[PDB]
Length: 347
Ligand SMILES: COc1ccc2[nH]cc(CN(C)C)c2c1
Ligand SMILES: [Cl-]
Ligand SMILES: [Cl-]
Ligand SMILES: [Cl-]
Ligand SMILES: [Cl-]
Ligand SMILES: [Cl-]
Ligand SMILES: [Cl-]
Ligand SMILES: [Mg+2]
View 1: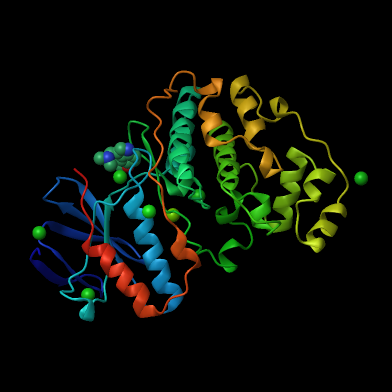
View 2 (view 1 turned 90 degrees about the vertical axis):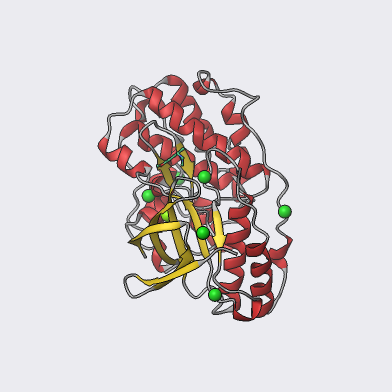
C-alpha cells in the first residue's frame, strides 16, 4: 500500500498517493476533477473523486458500472484507466473512489470552430472514431453519447473517445436548443423502439457532416423541430419502418406528417469529396437495421489511405450480466471494492 497525503482544495478533501503531485482543480454532479503530475509514469493526469458514490442503489450500481467499463477499455482510440485507488484500509471503512486517466486538452469542438480542415483531416479524424467504435461494438457495448465534446484531440490530430453514456442524462438536459440532443438517433430521441449499437453510427454521421461544413447538421430548437429537420433530409418513413415502431401513438404522429422524399446529398454538401457524400448516405439512414456498421465503414474507399485490416483490433469479451441483477447497496459496494483492489496497471 502506498503512503497517502491529505489536503483541502476548493472545499474538498483530497487524500491521494504520494506519486500524484501539484494537484490543481479543473472542474466539478458526477464528481470533482484535478490535474496532477504522476511521478511514477511521467504523464499529466486527471484525478476524479466521485461524489457520493454509494448514496443509493442506483448510484452504487452506476459506480460499479463505470469502473467495470473503464477497466475493460484497452485501445489506442478509447480512453483507458491508468489507476484507481481508495485511502480505505478495509471494506468496513470504504467510502471514497478515485479514478485516474490521461489529462485531455482540446476536444473536437475547439478544432471544428477554430481550424480550416482539409479533406485529409476529415478522413483521419473519422477513421479513428470508427476504429475505436469497431472495438467498442465488438464487446457489445453501446456508447450512446457520441458528440464533439466527448472526443479528445491533440496537436497531431490523434483522437480518443471518452465519457461513455452511463444512462445518466435527464429530461431537463435534453430539452430545447441544446447540443446534448443534436447528435442522437431519432429512434432513441423519441423512444420509438429498443435501440442497439446502430445509434452510435447515426452520431458519427452527424459529426462527419459538421466537420465538412463547419455547421451543426440538425440544430433543433426542441424534439419535434429536430425531427422535422431530420425527415426533410432523409425522407419520411415507409411502411417497412413504421412496422418497427412500438408506440402506436408515435406511429400515429409520424403518419400525421406530409410525406417527403430523401434529398440529394451532393446538393446539400456542396463541393465535398464524392466518396464522403457516399459514406454519409450510408450512415444517415432512418431505419437503423439498414445503416452501415463500423466494421463495414472502415473498408469504405473514403479511408483507402489509412485502412489496415491487420491493425484494427477487436475487444476481449465483456460480461454485462450484472445489469439485470438485483442487489443491495452494500453488495454493490463490496463488488466495487473487489474491483478497486484487483486493478493491475498497464505496462
Ligand atoms: C491531449 O489529448 C490527446 C488526445 C488524443 C491522444 N492520442 C494520444 C495521445 C497522447 N497520450 C500520451 C495520451 C493523445 C492526447
Ligand atoms: Cl505513491
Ligand atoms: Cl488512454
Ligand atoms: Cl475511503
Ligand atoms: Cl458537443
Ligand atoms: Cl402527404
Ligand atoms: Cl468480462
Ligand atoms: Mg462529456
